Length: 50
Length: 80
Image (cartoon, rainbow over all chains, first blue to last red; front, side, top):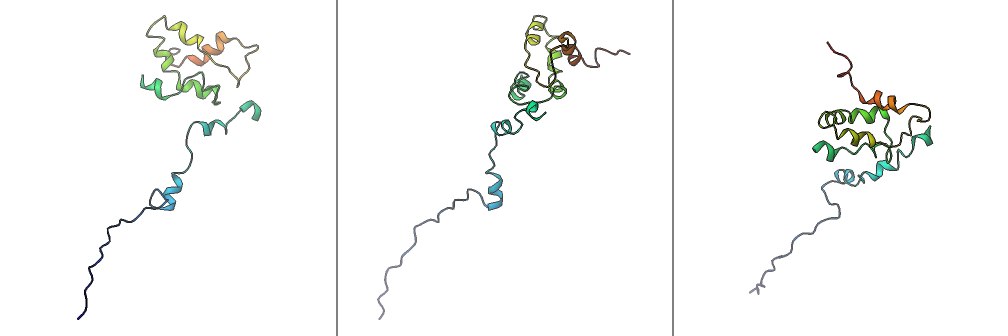
């Protein structure tokens, strides 16, 4: 004598994270800024070094 | 042409960055001897194309020999 309610099916998908890759280790390698302007400010002048 | 678009030019490998003159001519010696044996009107192009030499002092050196010493390989000095 039990009134059966209609079941509720979940129509929602799981959400993603802020880490854009799998690990936090693999993701850390892909945050190093690469370019030709980064080598520019490191080697700046040899005569200033000399 | 693929060598030209990938490797940076000789003028700003000595001005923006600072590479050394043994290392700068080692990359750009096969190209500056293929173009000199291609056409003779290109002979006036490359030798005008020169940047500032901040590593060595050009004040009482002769550039008639300083450019001439760094341009030649062992291919055109020794013969057997």
